[PDB]
Image (cartoon, rainbow, N blue to C red; front, side, top):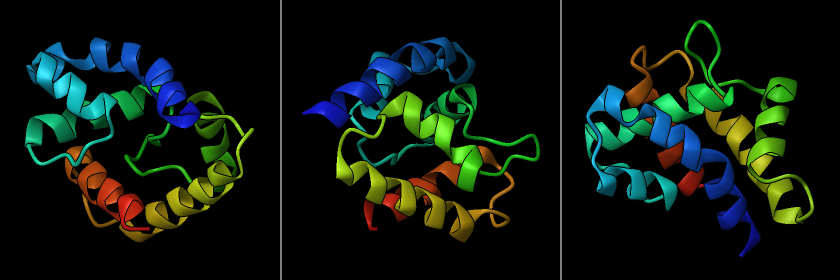
Length: 119
C-alpha cells in the first residue's frame, strides 16, 4: 500500500534525525513510522520533532493549514490517490481544531493525530 510506503520514505530519515533529541529507542522509531497511536510522551515528541523537520509546524508552533499544508502532503503522499484528498481535508480540519490549545508541540501532535485517526 502506497500511502503507508510514501510516508515511511519521507519521514523515516527525519525521525532518525530526531531520535537523540528525545532519547528515543528503536521501538519509538517504529511506533512513529507505522503511524500507531502515540501513547507515550517520547513517541509524541519524536513525531512532533519529525513533523517540524518536514515543514508542518509554523514558527509560532502551530500546524500549517491551507496552502502551507500542501508541500507537506506532496512530500509525504502526493496526490495520485483520491484518499489523499480526503486526508488533506482531515489534516486541515484537525489542525484548525487543535491549534491554540497546546503550546507544547508533543501535546499538539498527540491531539492532532488523535483527531486525524478519528476523522
